[PDB]
Length: 93
Length: 97
Ligand SMILES: [Ca+2]
Ligand SMILES: [Ca+2]
Ligand SMILES: [Ca+2]
Ligand SMILES: [Ca+2]
Image 1 (cartoon, each protein chain N blue to C red):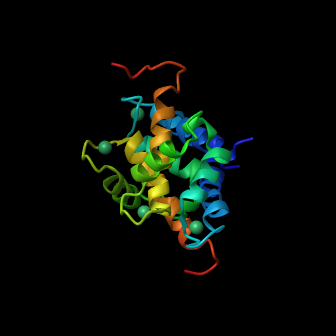
Image 2 (tube, each protein chain N blue to C red):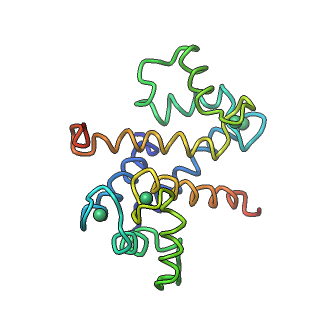
């Protein structure tokens, strides 16, 4: 009935699907971020699944510099992706 | 299938579903925000669909003070809802205290 509320639930559940695998269950480490990105957001990195790309992404996302991505930082990341899609919604910039 | 990519697509399209109804097609005015909230996010305001609630929400979301909610401000809003949902992922507050 409410696709946007369902979308939010997917955002929440997908985080935990990977954040709970290793160490802090509420934060994504490098390995968990790698798996989330490759499996759940393959269109984002595309062919850039190398270690250099993942280190750059980690540094971009880890705003509080604790070496992991928490839920707030993850939401900022997803917001950035949405904003990029927003820029091309009309079929031109 | 990639549910998270589908979720992002819905997040983007739902904005434009309402933002393009009046005036600036890339921003939600009060009227458009009301429609979006009531129809797409009824759980957020719940029973608080009065004018006082909607002015409060607009003030809370309109960070740049241009009287409307742009895409960036909308993302901040959805992020806050996601964080609130995150607190009850287990069906109780497992991150509290
Ligand atoms: Ca973890
Ligand atoms: Ca961090
Ligand atoms: Ca508008
Ligand atoms: Ca604004």
